[PDB]
Image 1 (cartoon, rainbow over the protein chains, first blue to last red):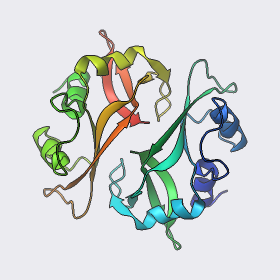
Image 2 (image 1 turned 180 degrees about the vertical axis):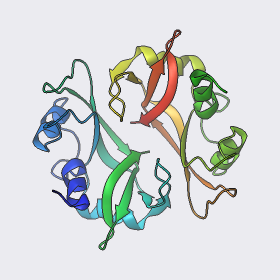
Image 3 (image 1 turned 135 degrees about the horizontal axis):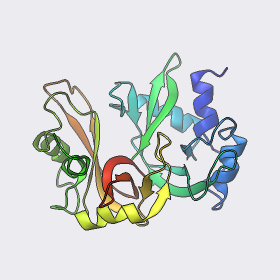
Image 4 (image 1 turned 90 degrees about the vertical axis):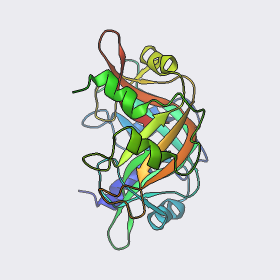
Length: 124
Length: 124
């Protein structure tokens, strides 16, 4: 079992590239980050900034999460991100994803000591 | 009680302006669209395009919703939107919102005949 922080890293962090490298980026990343094992994870965002910069969001703008929790934080600056969403004829175990690159603020829920991201809520 | 389509219009449509008019836009709009009556709605997005253009998204890119439903659609083009999120010392009945303007693709769930938006899923 993963810690919540490590799960966030596995699902949402890609500091190895400044942006999605091709239209196949999501197909590749959803598979290699183990998000297509038991089901096709329907929606998932990757962040192309340093882990330090993403962790730093937990000390930025405190805002509500979509579910009403009060431990969400919005990045002061925009960040390079990639949205991955099931599309076309995606059907487990043949998952297929649309890759959409953007530059947006991210909103994450933070927990723990150290206080780090544990859930990706949205991007603006 | 509202139809799902009318609720979407009340919560998410603002064709009267090309973008949020001030930092107080969300405070004003969340109140006047009756989203602060029983609770402070934590998060809500307004779309500044014509109703026709937003309805048209139901005939655009079919993608998964965050919850795994298959009736979501992503706009081919970006749209002017405003994200409203509770912030600071927001506490019912004294709701307070952060206003964040952006240009992004929208993702909506569609239902019915006519097939129209009934839920705002996310923006990319």
